[PDB]
Image: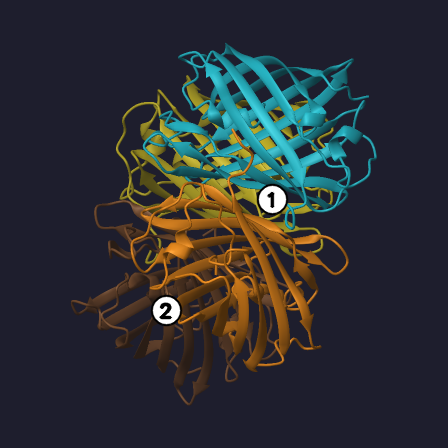
Chain colours: A brown, B orange, C cyan, D yellow
């Protein structure tokens, strides 16, 4: 794992049965927990749903881990790891996502599948009334020899208020790696620039691991 | 539009825990008797490493006997057809999202199905294939925001006894505006009647009848 | 131990959003016909500031017609009786936890009921009293760790149309060892047949029949 | 209204799986440091047949260190006080509903607490008393319909390793009109400091600090 790495990805998926595809390129510093990328809609544009539901699917290797917390993700390379996630929104909209992450030289390669269902037509997702994800705190922990990650967060809405979502992620390293203890990863994901119909999106994330209070 | 004897043709593309597969099927049924059967063949991703039972309820409420006093949303929706979306949340956290776009070509219904399941534990009854069958169930149907919803929480019986629960949440969307029904129910019973060892071939049956529950 | 005509006496103590209340009731029913009725009167905490409908399904599966081919967990449990626990999760986050300890004195069932609901929003149908009635329902009963479980998703019809859903999760506990049944169903239909303006007095009815689903009905 | 050192007096009445109990406690804390401690005494229903840990987070966000840039909903609410309601939904189906009416008498906060837990399985970690402690947690507070909400998904560490998860959903209600805060967080760490064999006596501690997340 080098101080400066690259990212290459393609997402294929569907929302309420309507398919789309997105590709991206970016860069980041795994030891600083920061990353950025440019995403382009390749199929299914203009997307008829809020782009925000996709952003957290677009790699916990980009998280600053302190010395005293075992780093599952940086350990998993060069072989890599995969993850599966269900994102259950409070109005019944559900998104299932998978990412198979490999490494080629200094570039991480993502193979992503995304499938969302049951988003109501008048809801904030289909009507594109989301502003941004709030900062969040993920709760990791081991179960049956694999790493799990839970984070219940929310999207701020146009006229104020919040639209909640529960994340449940399973992380699976390619090879056996040292498993960590119960810890946290704080997140802050932001869309810094985009064109009108989100065909082009510049996305950033900042993430740091910690163990909660005393600090 | 609906004939007493119809045919079914389908293809499902999907993935379970990130591992892709594909299944095609042909079948037949009687929409007015609420009965149907089909033969399914795994075309890609075999041998399937998960319990086939998680697929079966994705493999058409037009095959449901509707009484006269209950509006039939599904038979009304043809020849144009309808689509549906469904989330299947299992009690151990495994979740399956599925969609079906149903069209009609002559006397044959055509299904375009996508199926995506995640977070099934390796030690669980799905990945370990220790499910026996779905129990009979009762779906609850109601209108919300101009479309028809269907909720049913049911369970799979397990090898050594016991049950593995799952909550279904389906949204039915007719392609044309049709008359919306009142709150009602649909009883179900789905069964795998035959299959080879690795479920490459599966003969699947379903019986369904609509009703209004216990009277006032 | 169970006669064709039995009587009912109960007292419920509870709270909704921290506001306590108490209700007592008397009634009668036919256990083998799955029918019952009762008169309930608010004794404390009136006038109730929440929709009465959230209480009704807490106000006894012994009042359900069981066919001969389905094992009756509840009629077996008497004269000793049984208890049950339930959580009712409404789709807007309102949660009600309830318990009922059911005893028998002669031909009268005695209920000791606790009811606690929290997180009902002020603008919701419960606090705004916008519920009409429970729809008919189909409960699912199955065994887990030697006790009988009962799950039912149902809904309340609302005053301007639409439905307000709720998930029931009930655990039934016989006081003595009884024969456990297989996976089966119980159809329900509960109705408020009469009530005064502030629901100080309520006449409540329930009809329930067990079955094994399709084929048949 | 809030001084650097305050006292705590409380009584909890409740039931778990239909079995009633009652607990009273006295304690003290520093609201501006986000720290508190208390001694609790089982008065009725002892010896408690369930894991004491399910009660501890019910035994006051006034004891949370709020930075200057984040509006303090709780310190504003006194001397009139505030109340809160909570449902705690454990991953095996055990559900606990709790309420606390918090008043102020001089320098002492007074809690009137009700606690009701249901559907805890006999073979589960609660009824088998296999919990070790709550992990540290991060609560998220946000406004909905003019009142303050608090959500936290956390877990209890267990006896042979592993974790037993629980989702908290809290509604905070000030008795008078106060300034509402923006979306923010409160980190928690609750610990039983000492206890006797059957938990009839328990010394409990909590440390809490509010923050706005990354970066900090």
Residue C29 sits above or below residue B23 on the image: above
Q: Secondary structure at mark 1?
A: loop
For this rendering, which residue is in front, C81 or B61?
A: B61
Tag of residue D83? none
Residues C97 and D64: in front is C97
| Residue depicted at x 49% and y 70% | B8
- Where residue D21 sits, quadrant-wise, is top right
The residue furthest front is B4
Q: Residues within 10 Å of mark 1 (few under 14, many from 20)?
A: some
Q: Which residue is mark 2?
A: A14
Mark 2: few/some/many CA within 10 Å (<14, 14-19, 20+): some
x and y percent of residue C165 in the render? Answer: 45, 39
Residue under pointer 1: D93
Q: Is residue A32 visible?
A: no
Q: Which quarter of the rendered picture does the N terminus of chain B lie within?
A: bottom left
Give the residue at x 72% y 26%.
C32
Mark 1 or mark 2: which is in front?
Answer: 2
Where residue C51 sits, quadrant-wise, is: top left
Residue A15: image location, x then y, percent: 35, 65
Q: How many marks?
A: 2
**Quick check: can you spot residue B103?**
yes
Disc 1 to disc 2, C-alpha distance:
32 Å
Q: Residue at x 30, y 73 (%)?
A: A36
Residue furthest to the bottom in view is A105
Depth check, front residue: B72 or B93: B72
Q: Is residue D63 left or right of residue A159?
A: right
The reply to whether label 1 and label 2 mark residues of one chain is: no
């Amino acid at each position: 794992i080098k101080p400066d790495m690259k990212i290459k990805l393609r997402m294929e998926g569907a929302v309420n049965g309507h398919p789309f595809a997105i590709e991206g390129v970016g860069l980041g510093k795994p030891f600083e927990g920061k990353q950025s990328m440019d995403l382009k809609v390749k199929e299914g544009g203009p997307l008829p749903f809020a782009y925000d539901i996709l952003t957290t699917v677009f790699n916990r290797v980009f998280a600053k881990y302190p010395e005293n917390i075992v780093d599952y993700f940086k350990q998993s390379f060069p072989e890599g790891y995969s993850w599966e996630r269900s994102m259950n929104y409070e109005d019944g909209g559900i998104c299932n996502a998978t990412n198979d992450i490999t490494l080629d030289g200094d570039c991480y390669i993502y193979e992503i599948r995304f499938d969302g269902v049951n988003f109501p037509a008048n809801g904030p997702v289909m009507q594109k009334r989301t502003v941004k994800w709030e900062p969040s705190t993920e709760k990791l922990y081991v179960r049956d020899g694999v790493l799990k990650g839970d984070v219940n967060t929310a999207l701020s809405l146009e006229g104020g208020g919040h639209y909640r979502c529960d994340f449940k992620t399973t992380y699976k390293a390619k090879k056996v790696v040292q498993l960590p203890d119960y810890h946290f990863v704080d997140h802050h994901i932001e869309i810094k620039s985009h064109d009108k119909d989100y065909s082009n999106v510049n996305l950033h994330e900042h993430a740091e691991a910690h163990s909660g209070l005393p600090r």
